[PDB]
Amino acid sequence: SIKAIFLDMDGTILHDNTASGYTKEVIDQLRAKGYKVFLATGRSYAEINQLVPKGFTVDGIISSNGTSGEVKAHNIFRHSLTQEAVNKIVQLAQQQHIYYEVFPFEGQRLALQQDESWMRGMVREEEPQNNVGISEWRSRKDALKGKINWVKTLPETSYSKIYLFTTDLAQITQFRQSLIDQQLSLNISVSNSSRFNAETMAYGVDKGSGIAEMIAHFGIQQQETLVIGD
Amino acid sequence: SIKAIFLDMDGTILHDNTASGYTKEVIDQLRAKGYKVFLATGRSYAEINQLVPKGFTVDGIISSNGTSGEVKAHNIFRHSLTQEAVNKIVQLAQQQHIYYEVFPFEGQRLALQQDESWMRGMVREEEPQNNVGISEWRSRKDALKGKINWVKTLPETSYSKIYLFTTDLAQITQFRQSLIDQQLSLNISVSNSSRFNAETMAYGVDKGSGIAEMIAHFGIQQQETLVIGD
C-alpha cells in the first residue's frame, strides 16, 4: 500500500491556470488523509516556488531533474558536477560549436558571452531547421530571448547540469558519444530527450535517484511509492 | 490498499485548459497501473462527456450528483424523482414564489413560462441581494441568461433533482423545512449548499450512494476506494 505519491510536473499547471486551485486542493486532501506528497520537477527549487500558488504545501520537492532535494525549505541533497567537468564540457562544446546551457542551482542558466553570436546564429530562423522538433526549436528561441545569463567567465558555483544542442545531427551524435566515452573520467551521466541534444549531470543522478533519496529520508520504501505525471 | 479512485469535479479542468492534458494523462497512467478510476460530478452525463478532451477514458462516471451511473456508455442506475413529487414540489414552489430549476437526466434544466416573470425579477439586480453569496448570485444570473428551457407544461420524463432558491431567508428556511417534513411522503432527500437554497433528489440518493453503487458494480469495497476533489 502506498505511503508516498510523487507528482512530476513543470509547475505551469500551478499558477492564472484555473486548475492550480484544484491541484492544490487535491494535494491538501491527500496529505490530510496521511499520504506524503512530493513534487518532482526539472525546474529549479526557486522557479517552482515562484510558480506555485500561495499556501501550496508538499512534504518535499526534488528539483533540477533529481539533483536537488528540499524538505521544509532545507536542502537535503544537492548533487553537483565537478568544476573541472563543467570547464571541460564547455571547452569541448565551444570548440565544436555545440550550443550549450550551464545550469546552476541558483540563478539563470548561463553561457560564455564569446559564444553568444554563433549560438544565436544556430536557431536564427523562425521555422525549425534540419528536422528539429517545434518544441525544442521554440525552447531555444525562448532561451536566447531572455533566459541565458551571458557571462565573461564561468562562475564558480555548484552546477546541476549542462544541456547541449545542435542542428548538425552527425556532430551531436558524435559529441554525445564523446561524453559517454568520458562518463567515468568526468563522473557524469549522459541523457538525451531528442536526437539533437544531450544533458550531463553527476554520475548516477536522475529523477529516480532523487525519488529514492527523498523516500529514504521519510523511511518509505520504493514499493510504497506511487509516481505519476510527466 | 486502494483499487478505486474517484475524482470529484465539475469538468471545466478538462476543456483549451492546458491542464486538461495533464489530468487525462494522469488518469491514463493510474489506469495503466491497474487502478479503476471514476469521475463523480454534479453535471449530467451528456455535459461531462462533451467537456472532456478526446480519448479521455474512465472506468465509469457517476453524474447528476450520484443519481446516474454509466459504464461503457451504458446506464447502470438512473434514480428519478416520481412525477407526482416533481409536480407537487413545483406547485408549492410556485405558490410561494420560490425560484426553481427542474433537472431532467437529458436536456436543459427547466421551469414554467408562467413563472418566468417573477423568477427573472427576483435576480434582476447586478448586485447580489439580501446577503446572497457572489457565486450563487452569478449562477442564477447565468442560468437565466441561457440555461433554462421555459416550458408551457412540465415534460413527463425522468428527473434527477429540483433546485430551490429565494432571496427571502425566512421563506426558504420554512420551505426547506416543509420539504423535510414531507421527506417520507414524497420519497425525497433534501440537501442545501447555502441558507438561500434547497435541493430535492430521490430518497437516500447522493454522491456517496452513487459511489457505493459504482464500486459494488466492480466488486470493490469502500475501504479500497479513495475519493478526492470537490
Image (spheres, coloured by chain):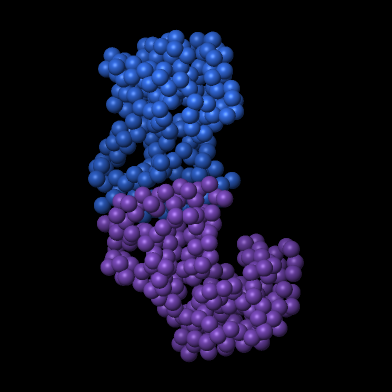
Chain colours: A purple, B blue
* Occupied quadrant, residue A89: bottom right
* Occupied quadrant, residue A132: bottom right
Residue under the point 48% across and 19% down: B99
**Residue nearest the observer in this picture, A8 or A181:** A8
Q: Quadrant of the C terminus of chain B?
A: top left
Total labels: the figure holds: 0
| Above or below B124: residue A178 | below
Residue under the point 55% across and 23% down: B123
**Residue nearest the observer in this picture, A160 or B57:** A160
Q: Position of residue B139 (x, y in %)?
A: 52, 30
For the question of whether residue B3 can be seen, the reply is yes
Residue under the point 64% across and 73% down: A148
Q: Position of residue A125 (x, y in %)?
A: 75, 66
Q: Position of residue A157 (x, y in %)?
A: 53, 82
| Above or below A168: residue B212 | above
Residue under the point 30% across and 32% down: B209
| Residue A150 appears left or right of B89 | right
Q: Position of residue B226 (x, y in %)?
A: 32, 46
| Residue A40 appears left or right of B184 | right
For the question of whether residue B83 can be seen, the reply is no
* Occupied quadrant, residue A131: bottom right
